Amino acid sequence: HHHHAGDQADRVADKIIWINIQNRIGQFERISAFEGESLLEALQRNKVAGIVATCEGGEDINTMLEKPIDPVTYGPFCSSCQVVVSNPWRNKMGNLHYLEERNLVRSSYPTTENSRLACCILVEKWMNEMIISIPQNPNSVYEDNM
Amino acid sequence: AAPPAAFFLYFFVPDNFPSAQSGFRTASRNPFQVQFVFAYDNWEYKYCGQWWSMGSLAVNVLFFVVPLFLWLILQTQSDQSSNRDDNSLTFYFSNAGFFFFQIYTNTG
Amino acid sequence: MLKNKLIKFKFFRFVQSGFYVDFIFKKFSEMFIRNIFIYSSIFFGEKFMIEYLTKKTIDSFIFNNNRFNFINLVESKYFLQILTLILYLFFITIFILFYI
Amino acid sequence: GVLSEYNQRLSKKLHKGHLVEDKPTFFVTSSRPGNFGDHIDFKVNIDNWFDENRVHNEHETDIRRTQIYTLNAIYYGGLLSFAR
Amino acid sequence: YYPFLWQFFILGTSFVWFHVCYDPWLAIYQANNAHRSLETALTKEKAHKKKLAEQ
Amino acid sequence: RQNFAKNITTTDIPKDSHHFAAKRSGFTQTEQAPFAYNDVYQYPKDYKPWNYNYKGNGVLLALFLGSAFSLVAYERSYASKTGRYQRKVQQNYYQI
Amino acid sequence: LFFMCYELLLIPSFLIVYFVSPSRRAIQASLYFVIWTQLGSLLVLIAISYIISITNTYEFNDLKYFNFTNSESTIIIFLIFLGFGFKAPIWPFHYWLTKTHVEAPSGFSIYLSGFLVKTALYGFYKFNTSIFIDIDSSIFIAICIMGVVDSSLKMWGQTDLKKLVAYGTIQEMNIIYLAFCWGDSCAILGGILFSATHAFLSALMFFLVDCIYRRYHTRSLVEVNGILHITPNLGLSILFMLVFFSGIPGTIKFISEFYIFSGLLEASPFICFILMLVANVLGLIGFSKSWFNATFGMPKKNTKYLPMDLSFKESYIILYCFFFLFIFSYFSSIFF
Amino acid sequence: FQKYPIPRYLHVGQWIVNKNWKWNTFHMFFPTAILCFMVWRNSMISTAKPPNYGEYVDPQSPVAPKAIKY
Amino acid sequence: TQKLDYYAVLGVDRLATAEQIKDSYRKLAMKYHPARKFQEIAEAYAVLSVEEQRRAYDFLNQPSPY
Amino acid sequence: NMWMYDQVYPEYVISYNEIHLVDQWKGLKESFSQSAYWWAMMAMVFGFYFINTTPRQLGIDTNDLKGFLGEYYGQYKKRSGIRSNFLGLDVTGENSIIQPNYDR
Amino acid sequence: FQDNQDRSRVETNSATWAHNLPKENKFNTETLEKQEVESRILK
Ligand SMILES: COC1=C(OC)C(=O)C(C/C=C(\C)CC/C=C(/C)CC/C=C(\C)CC/C=C(/C)CC/C=C(\C)CC/C=C(\C)CC/C=C(\C)CC/C=C(\C)CC/C=C(/C)CCC=C(C)C)=C(C)C1=O
Ligand SMILES: CCCCCCCCCCCCCCCCCC(=O)OC[C@H](COP(=O)([O-])OCC[N+](C)(C)C)OC(=O)CCCCCCCCCCCCCCCCC
Ligand code: FES
């Protein structure tokens, strides 16, 4: 940030990153997120259906959200946070990490070339008014029902 | 060159107790210096067989074959020791298992 | 002798530089330092002979073996595995019995 | 490295192990004499080794000439050792 | 560009060929038969003669 | 973080109060309230920060007594080693 | 009980690295430490089970009345050498040691270099001395010398000071491990003395690295230099440590070098010269460059955050290390 | 070089003059001389010297060099 | 020489009209006309100007996104 | 570590004042080309002194032949390093890495 | 050696019986071409 003594606080409305969502039932949703956060955290705080998130984002030390990805990271753990990103934003995202691609292509449900794991996305300024679709994600284990 | 924007930084375990010696005054770090600090640890090879020709092929081969050279030189000098009846390269057994300065006493 | 190339500045600076012996010796020492020390020692030794050949060989073997593994069992694979186990355990045992 | 060279040479597309053209190919010399007409309908070349066997080093050819001399010299040196 | 210097180069290549094919085989051959030497035989003979003399 | 108490009971902290006087009067409508304590540390005026300010004799006395005990113990050990009650002193000693 | 006490040392070490280290990279370093040290312990366990099953006894004395054949002796010596060289780091197995020193807390690093690795020298010695082995020790000697050469050749290209100290530890540990490759001969005296020498030298060097890290919040040559001219006591300690590591003839480092090098020169002249040149010149030059550059220069960057000099605790610890080296140069000659 | 200020907290040795240097010189010099005298007095016990002018070493005297009886 | 990407050199996407290529070449030519970069620009524009040549170049590439 | 790092005036670990010579090979060429002059001057000096001088009678003191030279030949006359062990241990001086060679 | 540029595995096999010319990947997200849609609309 950048502030001077005596200045007033900025508005949360001006700092909101907007995410546009097509549901599993074909309906449209609008979600508020913030920079420095993962897409999974915003989606779960806003209670968006269609994501299972069995592993709840992965480990806590060497994560996929750090801007340079650490070599000895383990990557995503469940591949159950998939979303489909529209063309401009997905093109700006870039090529997939090899571990993320391995987890994406190994899922039990069909995927696409625009598929992307939500917990592997760090929300940025240029993601404002980004369009995504969330078809329902697969279940994995017995405890998913609990 | 522009200063780096993304690079590996220092990291600490959760709930780490900070070091507070000499008044606990920490300065901002230099991106180039931190980049150099963490570059070598994270450096890796790109393709199979890249190491052999990386730098000097002859020098790398010589470094690779160093242990064999040492073994061969030791073998030659063992040949020299054998005919001169010098100390050979063997595990000498002359104390019959008695240790260097060991207390050997009995009870009763 | 009416001309003398030894009174010109080229020869003068050659002699003043100590016959360029220091410059020649330092250039070869730089080549030794760079090549041997940096490349051979740290990169070759640590990265290939120590890091790679001890850890990354096993790591890459495991990764490449897992390249051919289905993480989720399917029914046809299960039945095929059972049948293959039966038939080819029998084959290997009878082959050892007969020709070995 | 040798492994990399083998890796690139492993992916070449061949017809039963031989690098040959998959279609009839005709070439004309644009500066040929006027009494030479069009190319006759005869498949004279099965391969395209005139274009495939290239390293594209026309900016440094004496280097390759020197390398060929060096290989010849090594072979001659072995033969001359035996003759000696 | 100097053909006789190139001939000297060829002679050097032949020298390297000969020494590469000569040195290691001779080294291992001599290292393999160190205990089968006249010096070892004479050492054993002298030791036995000393023992028999001071017997 | 440190959690020890600073108002010790063994002795009173050497300090002076003439330095850093408080205002206590003549305040305006915009300035801040004055501070409360203002006391500062006072050094013994014979203290040298660049050396040990040690004026005791205990270390020297202990080392001297240890060395003297070493000497007398060696004398006793040498007398016992020669099979004598005390050292037999020769009438002439020469360079080793 | 010997083997059990050797095995008991792993859990506290792993717990200290796991729960006390502040660096985040120490989580994987502890796993590396565990996996290499346990592979070595597994090799030692195989050898111990061999000895126990063949000779149904648990006393070192009873081994005097039982003979092992050539095959069993070769298997046992190879197993114990490799297993104890996993912990006392031989050439091909020091990745765990490098990572663990780089990521571990300073106090445990002092304990690991100073004392823990020595536990491998002791046990090996015992199992080396209780058995009659009829093999040529050239392979083990070559492995140890390769360790020394490889470690000392890598000192120039180190900017982290802690990694440099770890490589010095590796080279002198391999030098000590070389001395036990001739059985119960007189070569063990130099190794026994040089174990204590390395203990104190490594403790001093890691303590100096800890002082630098706590003062300047870094241990990289590209970030800190001119340790002299600001906090001069630390720079003086660094220079005196460099002298003692170089091995002035007044200390026990020189004595240990003299012992081992006299024996090696008689056993192998060209090998002795090669090892001496590689260890005491090239590695010394790299070590000295990396340490001199940090001591000298101008500390211009952050004057608002520059630290104070050594405390009494650090000064007395450094002085005691120096005093122990100098005064243990005067121990009784009945031993050694 | 022109003099520049040195921080008071630093125990460094730029441009330092001790006003009591005469007594300190005395009290560092004389005990040093006494210690060196004691060291020299101890060391003269183990000091050797060739025979003086006009003197010869009797080969059969006890001080003469000796061999070993096996 | 080395392998070169003509679209990256001209600063245009693959699905760009011919007139866009001409405009990009003119914009890049005003700058570097008075060495190596201008040669790369000229080679890329020469290949991509002809529809048949551009089609043949595109067929062999099989481009990847991003 | 190819640079002497410093917060003021960092430097390269090796200085090259004679940089007008680009590399070591041209440096060697230049050094030999310019040292040919010194070779010629030395040759002229030696030619002068060889034309205008007679060799001297230099050697050891002829009155000390039983001294330095006598001991050297006496060492080979008395092959003392290959005598039998004084304890009778069936070893000689030849059974060592550092051994006498009296027929060298 | 582990090559991170090679991301193929048994999960990504995309060989189908119907298609004599194999498809680029196993995502059946291929759209129609512009001229085909126009021709069919004209029909
Ligand atoms: C002027 O230096 C030089 C330096 O500075 C000392 C240098 O830094 C360098 C730069 C060097 C480097 C960068 C690294 C290279 C490493 C080296 C070790 C090169 C060092 C080179 C030298 C020290 C120069 C020496 C070489 C020559 C050619 C000197 C030439 C001397 C003469 C011509 C004297 C003339 C001798 C004559 C005429 C002998 C003829 C004999 C008779 C008349 C009969 C009488 C003699 C006898 C009976 C006995 C002698 C017989 C023989 C066969 C011996 C003769 C052999 C000789 C070599 C004289 C160079 C090139 C150099 O160049
Ligand atoms: C057989 C004899 C062979 C002789 C071979 C030639 C030998 C020449 C003398 C020895 C070598 C001297 C090299 C130059 C050293 C000084 C360089 C320098 O800085 O110069 C600047 C000095 C001081 O000048 P300056 O430095 O103030 O500036 C002058 C301007 N510059 C820099 C351009 C030179 O000047 C000189 O040295 C003057 C030139 C000296 C010329 C000597 C000629 C000698 C002729 C032969 C005599 C032979 C007698 C008989 C011998 C018999 C026994 C052998
Ligand atoms: S929530 Fe498990 S992979 Fe993203």
Image: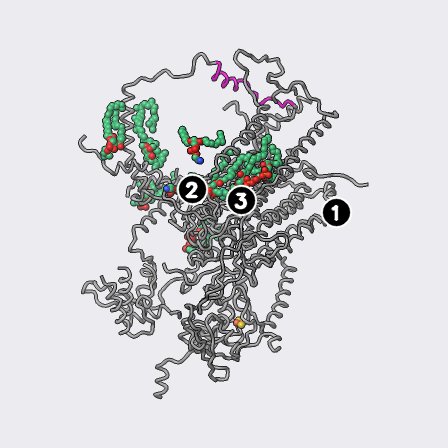
Q: Chain of mark 1?
A: G
Q: On the image, numbered disc 2 is attached to which residue?
A: H15
Query: Please, which residue is most extreme toward the front here?
Result: F26
Residue type marked 2: Trp
Coloring scheme of the render? one colour
Q: Residue at x 63, y 65 (%)?
A: C89
Q: On the image, numbered disc 3 is attached to which residue?
A: F46
Question: Looking at the picture, does residue C59 appear above or below residue F73?
Answer: below
Q: How far from the left and from the top, in percent, is residue C69?
A: 55, 67
Residue type marked 1: Thr
Q: CA distance from mark 3 to mark 1?
A: 73 Å
Residue D73: image quadrant is top left
Q: How far from the left and from the top, in percent, is residue C100?
A: 63, 57
Q: Nearer the viewer, residue A53 or A141?
A: A53
The magenta stretch spans residue A52:
no
- Is residue A56 found left or right of C20 in the rendered image? right
Magenta part of the protein: which range? J66-86
Question: Looking at the picture, does residue C20 appear above or below residue A27?
Answer: above
Q: Chain of mark 2?
A: H
The kind of secondary structure element at disc 3 is loop
